[PDB]
Amino acid sequence: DRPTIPWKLIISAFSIAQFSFESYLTYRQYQKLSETKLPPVLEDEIDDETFHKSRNYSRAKAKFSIFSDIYNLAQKLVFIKYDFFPKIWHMAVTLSNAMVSTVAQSLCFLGLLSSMSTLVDLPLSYYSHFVLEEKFGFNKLTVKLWITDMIKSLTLAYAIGGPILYLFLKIFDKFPTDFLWYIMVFLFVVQILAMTIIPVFIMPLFNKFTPLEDGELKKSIESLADRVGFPLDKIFVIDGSKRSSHSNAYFTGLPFTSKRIVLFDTLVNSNSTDEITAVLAHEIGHWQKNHIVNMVIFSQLHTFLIFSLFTSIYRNSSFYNTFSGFVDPVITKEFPIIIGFMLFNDLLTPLECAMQFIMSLISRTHEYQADAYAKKLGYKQNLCRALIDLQIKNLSTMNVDPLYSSYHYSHPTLAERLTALD
Ligand SMILES: [Zn+2]
């Protein structure tokens, strides 16, 4: 536990290492998608034509994935070896006029930084939407709406992100010796408010929430709810058609309290008729077995590990000194917590890989249990046809690499979800 260790080399080595590992995964997946032509348990229920089209969708996804990784590894390594952070700090504070200048310039640094991460990402985000998924008729948005969404995301990020971060940072000042349990509780309470505030206040700005047109489907879902429990405030059908013809469904409720069921516009349309309910049995499965409880708990362990280790490396950095020590246009005074946190974030990357395996696996077995639970309710045959139709219209990957799926896939392979039931 001490200051002088070669940080530059280690961080560059880690980023390259885990990029290479991720490149290996993506490589295997590309192999299988291009070579294999048959699913074992889906050889009858997958059109030979819509199978090839799905091979192509996944191909382009992988290609773009690798280019996106190289791009994000390239700008990082350049950011590192050329000490690009100090420079942004100076340029940020320089653009602060009105005095209303303060001790927490950290917010300024992050203000310009995140805005740069946006503009540098912009080209990729544009390609993915207006090329990768326009080529497969998935994207239904105009540039007008895309840009407006970007601006709304940044404006919100500052509006509520600034205040929360500020308090988060000043909590370190009040407790320089024992901050752990305080910032722990802080993140917990922000989490609770988060799941309650984003759906109620933030989402309405993105999509138009309308209540489910009273009739058949409303009654069906209402009946499944009353049967298995009392968790149901109301049902809304969001307009997710405006973005792309992708489908999904979820419920938003502050647990444990009333829960609202949101259904995607493309879902109620003619892809899922009332196999929709089998799906909702699956999604009620997550609630019944207290998975959300297991997830917040497994999340708190993670956070504790992270900020337990933080105590070790929030003292001295190779980068600017903060209280001429041997290099140029450096930054001075109080050590700034935000910076030590970021570099620490890129120090952990291997730990994250480990917990990427762990989290992906837990989610997978949660889906397993929810499906089995849908069988318990008799929605087995409809649930099967639901998942199959989703994979058909979303051109999801048919036969995947075990390792690649073990790392990335939070949901088990379709074939793997069926064999557990069918
Ligand atoms: Zn699920």
Image (cartoon, rainbow, N blue to C red):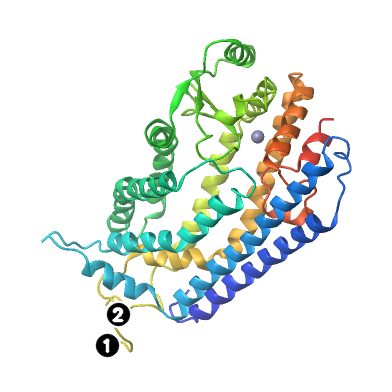
Instruction: First in sequence, mark 2 or 1: give its number.
Output: 1
Spot occupied by residue 346 in the image (x, y as percentages of width and height) = 51, 66
Q: Which residue is mark 1?
A: 324
At horizontal 64% and vertical 12% (from top left) the residue drawn is 227
Nearer the observer, 152 or 85: 152
Number of numbered discs on residues: 2
Q: Quadrant of ligand 1?
A: top right
> Dot 1, crowdedness within 10 Å: few (<14), some or many (≥20)?
few
Spot occupied by residue 382 in the image (x, y as percentages of width and height) = 75, 23
Image quadrant of residue 414?
top right
Eye-nearest disc, 2 or 1: 2
State whether residue 172 appears in this view.
Answer: yes
SS at badge 1: loop
Nearer the observer, 311 or 392: 392
At horizontal 46% and vertical 58% (from top left) the residue drawn is 122
Nearer the observer, 6 or 249: 249
State whether residue 312 appears in this view.
Answer: no
Mark 1 is on which residue type? Ser
Q: Which residue is mark 2?
A: 330
Callout 1: CB less than 8 Å from ligand 1? no
Looking at the image, residue 64 sits to the left or right of residue 91; the answer is right
Looking at the image, residue 32 sits to the left or right of residue 117; the answer is right
Mark 2 is on which residue type? Val
